[PDB]
Structure formats: structure tokens, C-alpha cells
Image (cartoon, rainbow, N blue to C red; front, side, top):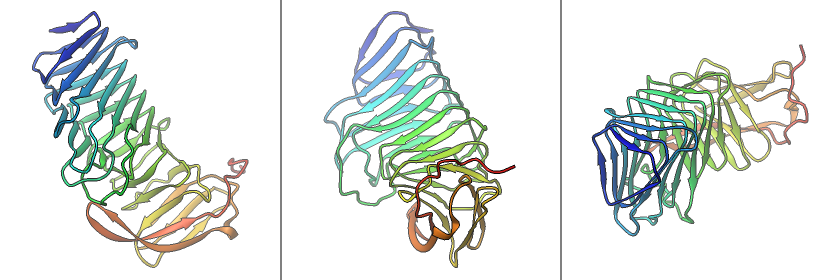
Length: 307
């Protein structure tokens, strides 16, 4: 219905009850509320949508509700320059279908936790062969360790077909609540901690940067592929009385608390250098005893396992 065929810039709050097809570039400025209630189609790859929150205002909402559908082969940027402990934002991407073969970038200046913000990616169906980014354009410090403003991906019982890349590079923490699938996908934890509380975790590789962490709140039956493991990061597993073992032939790290967690970290690690310790983590406002594994060594030069 609404077709953007020439570079367009719109001002103020926007509520799209029509299907929106963008083949050029659409820019949304000076609005505290951007709503796409039906189709939002961005194609071909050179097309783009950029939603800029109104500056120096209290609340910001970007919404793709369950009535909507997202089909992006170009570039969708959601940017909010508002920052500070009183910031309230609601970036709620919950379309019936979320199909991305291009780039989606969440670019926020308010990345600290708070009491009231929501950052949600939880459609019914999730399809990503491109790149989804969460980046910071702020400089906030002194996080209050609250439960709001934590990017939460998926939900219990729904799946996420991640054939491409999810880049997490903005905040102290992120939550993965849905079931990831597809063998080619990667989740890159470039800053902060990733907490996983999901029914299963299939196919993807979790790549940890330095001074990041992966924490599984509940064990999954799948072996979880994690790469980048070295003295700069850790894998945490919820539960008390933690023990662990590393198999040099398969490259699999097995952690046992009250449940069994299995991580494929690669071959080449020396198990005699590894150690573990009990700590306490916070997840969705509750404290959990957690067993941490520190490999205490660099990434091996060759991660391949013997046949």
C-alpha cells in the first residue's frame, strides 16, 4: 500500500496500519513512537529504514507487534540517542514472522539495566541469514544491576532459525530464551555476559570475546559449540557441588552440578591447567549458585580433533 520509491524523511510519531514496502531509503526522525502494525518490507539489499528516536525525551517505542511481519533484505537501523538512568525505551520486535537476509542494527545510548525498559526480539517465527547487531552509542557506567533493558531473544517453546550472525556488543548482559537452531549460525558475545535459559540449543556456535561469559541457566541435552574459550572468558553452569571433565579426544567439556552441561570447545586444550569454582550469578532478578570453568590457557593453535 505505502511504497517508498524515493529517498524519504518523515517527522514525528508514525503509526503504519498499511503495508509498507521500502525500495529506496526511509528515514524516521523526531518521533517518540514508531509503529509498524502490518507488513514492513525492505528490499532490495540497497534499501534501508532508519528510525531515529526523538532526542531529549522520556520514552521511546519501536514496535513490530504480533499483527506485523518483517521481511528485510536491506538495512534496518533502530537508533536511540537518549541516555541516562531515567531513560525508558521499548524496542519490541515481535512480528508474526521475522525474516532477515540483510542487516538489522539496534544502536542505543542507554545500555545499562533499568527498572522499566524492554528490549525484546520474540516473533512467532524467526529467520536470519544476515546479521543482527546490538551496538552501543553511549558511555553509561555504574550499572544498577536491575532487570529492565536486557535484550531478551526468543521465548520458551519458540525456535530461532539463525543461519547467519547475531552480534552482541552493547551491554552487561543479554538473555537467550528461545531455542536456537541451524548449523551455520553464530552468536558473537563481543561485550558482556550471555545467559541462556532455553529448552534446547541446536546447531549454532557461540563465539566468546575477551572478558565475556556464557552462562547456561538450565542444561540442554545438546552439545553446545563454543569457541574463543581462553583465560579471558568463562563458561558458567548453574548448580551446586560442581565438577567438570574435559575429553581430549572429542574436545567436549562436561560440567556436572545437579544437571549435565556439555560444551564442544574444541580439541587441543590441556585439562591439567583447567580449574573451576562456585560463584553466584543473577538472572531475571534471582540469585543462582553457579559453577564456573576457567581453562587458564590460550586458545590452542589447532582445535581439530583426531579421527
